[PDB]
Amino acid sequence: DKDVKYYTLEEIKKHNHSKSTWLILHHKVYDLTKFLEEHPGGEEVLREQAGGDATENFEDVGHSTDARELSKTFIIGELHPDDRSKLSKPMETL
Ligand code: HEM
């Protein structure tokens, strides 16, 4: 999974189902849906932080390098650039 489709926080918080198990690991949007059962450890752990900050876990365990790699193929997007260093503005329409 190799692209950066800049997604909005709402979007990430709208993929927490089962076939879109996303999460935010270091201001980045990952997708481990096809990795849920393909993850050496569990799957439900990726759901406990689905569309949410699993970074606490990722670091608590202090993951191996081979895992740091699948991260690169699990990114599907990044936190919007209007929402990386602000997260505080209106929208306005017409
Ligand atoms: C980029 C996303 C992730 C990738 C690519 C990934 C990949 C891996 C790999 C390759 C291992 C090593 C297997 C072993 O030690 O036998 C591992 C272990 C593990 N992972 Fe992940 N992982 C990811 C995210 C997560 C997250 C967010 C959680 C928790 C919510 C988690 C919890 C664990 C646990 C519990 C283990 C077993 C070893 C231990 O921590 O004692 N992983 N992971």
Image (cartoon, rainbow, N blue to C red):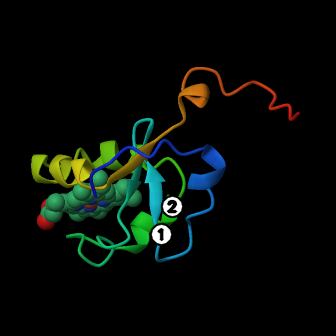
Name the residue at 50% across, 64% down. 48
Q: Residue furthest right?
A: 94
Question: Cα distance, mark 2 to mark 1?
Answer: 9 Å
Q: Upstream in the sequence, badge 2 or badge 1?
A: 1
Q: Nearer the viewer, residue 52 or 73?
A: 73
Q: Mark 1 points at which residue?
A: 20
Q: Position of residue 38 (x, y in %)?
A: 23, 75
The image quadrant in which ligand 1 is located: bottom left
Dot 1: few (<14), some (14–19), or many (≥20) neighbours within 10 Å?
Answer: some
| Residue sitting at the far top | 85
The answer to whether residue 16 is left or right of residue 88 is left
Q: Is residue 74 left or right of residue 29?
A: left
Specify whether tag 2 is near ligand 1 (CB below 8 Å).
Answer: no
| Residue at point 61%, 45% (across, down) | 9
Label 2 crowd bin: few (<14), some (14–19), many (20+), radius 10 Å: many
Mark identifier at residue 75:
none
Picture coordinates of residue 22, whole percent (x, y): 46, 60
Percent across and percent down for residue 54 are 44, 50
Total number of numbered discs in the rendering? 2
Q: Which of pointers 2 and 1 indicates the residue nearer the eye? A: 1
Q: Which amino acid does label 1 sit on?
A: Ser
Amino acid carrying label 2: it is: Ala
What residue is disc 2 on? 50
